[PDB]
Amino acid sequence: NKFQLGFSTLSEELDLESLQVKGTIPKWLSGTLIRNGPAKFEVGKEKFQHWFDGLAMLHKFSFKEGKVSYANKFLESKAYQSARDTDKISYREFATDPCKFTDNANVNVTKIAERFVAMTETPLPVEFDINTLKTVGVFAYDDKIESGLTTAHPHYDFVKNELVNYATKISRSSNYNVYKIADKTNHRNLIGSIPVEEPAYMHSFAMTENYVVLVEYPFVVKPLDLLLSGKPFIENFSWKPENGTRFIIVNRQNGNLVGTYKSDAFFAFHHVNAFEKQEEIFVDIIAYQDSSIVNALYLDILRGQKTDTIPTSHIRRYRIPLSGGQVEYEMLSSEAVELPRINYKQYNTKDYRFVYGISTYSASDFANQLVKIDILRKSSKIWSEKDCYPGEPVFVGAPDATKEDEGLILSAVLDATNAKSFLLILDATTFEEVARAEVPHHIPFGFHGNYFE
Ligand SMILES: CC1=C(/C=C/C(C)=C/C=C/C(C)=C/C=C/C=O)C(C)(C)C[C@H](O)C1
Ligand SMILES: [Cl-]
Ligand SMILES: [Co+2]
């Protein structure tokens, strides 16, 4: 297992004004890339069981006139602080329990009320200073919306300047609570509540011009099992394919229920994009046949000699006829893909042509390719390098760009032979390297990051 290092702890935290750059970083890149992910997979003798359990570490790539600065710090969550100060796992994670939700916000980062927050799937984000990467603390919402489970995949409406997300109240009468947050406030407005007997694990959701679409995979929990069983969070979820998948369509301006539609069972972590066209909604999803991927992302499998056991996902375009009818899909590409990203700022909620992601096709290795899928031409461009494992491709559009793929792709890449990571900058159009910046250590395999101007 050459990539074993990507799932090993990084204890080193440093701050460097300049990384060694090769190539040239465009002058117009003047923002900051923040990467989030797990970077500590044990506390004393106690090991975290699952990739999703690792204690959050932020990585900062800040750009000035062709130079790039780097800093990394562990998020000083109560989860981290308690582990550091008692050498005991102290909060319940995705798949590990101690020997009252974790604030181990290891999944994604965004801005709420002009503040930088790290996010996981527990109710409250964790605020951090982008200058220092210091932790300010739990970011409280100012509202009466009940939640136990949420996403670290909020959507953002650039027209209305609203963050959009949902949170599940998990109780004997559970609710999916769809909400929005206006710029310069931490108050969430409830759009709508959908009552549900057995809440589904929905890592992300779709947003169109007029709608939120919750795609309810039949991977579901009995609320009382979560409240009372001895078992870590994710062990309480069951695959029930007889339920099918349910597309719940909510008007995200007035909370009206547009309708519910069923397809055959499938599972997904990541939506790609969705859009309305005539009397139809198209929903592009990185779909697995079932939920078995969840058990494949336990560390003993990820570190083991059986990684061809890890199920592949593919881009499915689901067509919802609002007129009425069963939801059918077609494949947009033959490539196995995860960690999808688009020209979000210009093409989220809109008809589009280009998806960036990591190849999980295993042509030559595990997760060793960046891929750019051309939906129109049904073709792909590939980036790879011997014994290198690239992270999520973050797209940044060029100034006054007239094309969907005019800009840069930023990917944190593990170099296994060098036992250190580099930031790869591709031109999004050619999908060829324009620069890289060396990091003095390995960046463990992370989840999501965002570029802030
Ligand atoms: C939400 C909830 C709980 C905690 C859930 C937790 C720790 C979820 C973590 C999700 C993560 C980190 C997912 C990451 C996905 C990345 O690709 C209790 C504390 C285990 C029980 C409570 O009733 C409900
Ligand atoms: Cl129950
Ligand atoms: Co995710």
Image (spheres, rainbow, N blue to C red):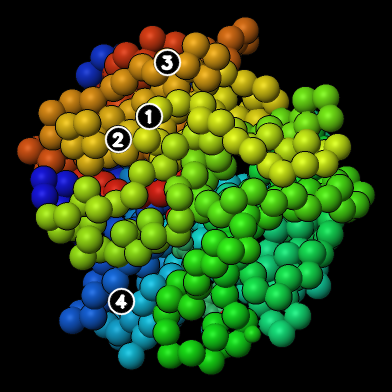
The earlier-in-sequence mark between 3 and 4 is 4
The earlier-in-sequence mark between 1 and 4 is 4
Residue pointed to by mark 2: 361
Residue pointed to by mark 1: 335
Q: Amino acid at mark 2?
A: Tyr
Residue pointed to by mark 4: 84
Q: Quadrant of residue 342?
A: top right
Q: Residue at x 38, y 29 (%)?
A: 335
Residue pointed to by mark 3: 379
Q: Amino acid at mark 3?
A: Ser
The earlier-in-sequence mark between 4 and 2 is 4
Q: SS at mark 2?
A: loop
Residue 31 percent across, percent down from the top left: 50, 30
Task: Judge the density around disc 1: few (<14), some (14-19), many (≥20) Cα neighbours within 10 Å.
Answer: many
Q: CA distance from mark 1 to mark 2?
A: 6 Å
Q: SS at mark 3?
A: strand
Q: CA distance from mark 2 to mark 3?
A: 15 Å
* Horizontal side, residue 230 vs residue 245: left or right: left
Task: Judge the density around disc 2: few (<14), some (14-19), many (≥20) Cα neighbours within 10 Å.
Answer: many
Q: Residue at x 31, y 59 (%)?
A: 296
* Horizontal side, residue 248 vs residue 224: left or right: right
Q: Quadrant of residue 216?
A: bottom right
Q: Are marks 4 and 2 in contact (CB under 8 Å)?
A: no
Q: CA distance from mark 3 to mark 1?
A: 9 Å
The mark found on residue 261 in the picture is none
Q: Is residue 402 visible?
A: yes
The earlier-in-sequence mark between 2 and 3 is 2
Q: SS at mark 4?
A: helix
Q: SS at mark 1?
A: loop
Q: Amino acid at mark 1?
A: Glu
